[PDB]
Structure formats: structure tokens, C-alpha cells
Length: 80
Length: 80
Image 1 (tube, rainbow over the protein chains, first blue to last red):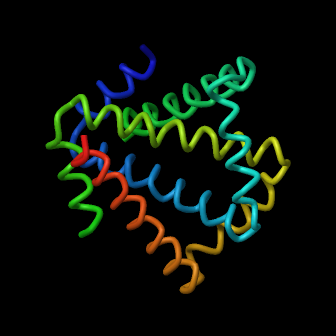
Image 2 (tube, rainbow over the protein chains, first blue to last red):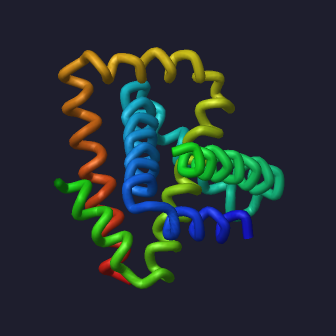
């Protein structure tokens, strides 16, 4: 449901603000991915990622992180 | 303009497919951020990021990476 609210805000904000926020996220993703390559960590990331299907603790940490991202995102849009 | 096409596809695909794709990206961002923390790389990432305003070469690499992300994203939506 926090994620539903994020989607609501994205799709109902002005096209100008939603576009800027999604581009911000795209750029951050690109930076992060590029950093991981620059530092040769790709295999390590991949392992760490598989865990999510099974590991309850990680699932909790990622879920908490996604909400933090949503909150920032929402703020950015409301902030203008 | 590649980014405009991404936005077009996001906002004009079914709400079901666009929501799933944006959630996929959110989860990936959360994984990446969490990984960087788990590995104590936060300061290093931050420096690497500042460069983007000035460094032509990085600007090119990130720009190429964003397009790759867009292409995958678009494919995901078209793929269903």
C-alpha cells in the first residue's frame, strides 16, 4: 500500500514533476550500476540479490529502504 | 529524447504494466543502495557522483547506461 500511494502520486502529479522525478531515479540507478562496475563488484551484488527470495531479514531491510525511497520521491513531487 | 520516449511508454502503457516496471526499478534501487551500505562504500559513491557535473567522460558513460536501462524498461512493458 505505501507503493500504491507512490504510484498514485506519480500518475497524478503534473507531468513536469513526475517526469523530473522518474529521470532523477533513472540517473541514480545508472550511477549506482556504473559505480558497481567501476569497482568490479558485479558478482558480489548478484549473490547478495538472490537472497531476497528466501531471507526474511533482508526482505525487511529492502522493504524499509523502498519506503524511504518512496517518501523522498513523494516529497520531491510535493515539494515541486 | 530517448528519455522522452521512455516517459511516453510509461505513461501510455497499461497501468498494470507501468506499475510493475516502476516497482521493479524501485526494488533494484533499494537493493543497490543497501548493497553499497552493506559493503561500507557510501563515501566512495558520493565522490564518484560529484564528478558528473564536470567530467565529460563519465557524463557519456552514464548517459549510455541510462539508455540501456530505458531500453530494458521499454522492453519489459512491451513484453508484458
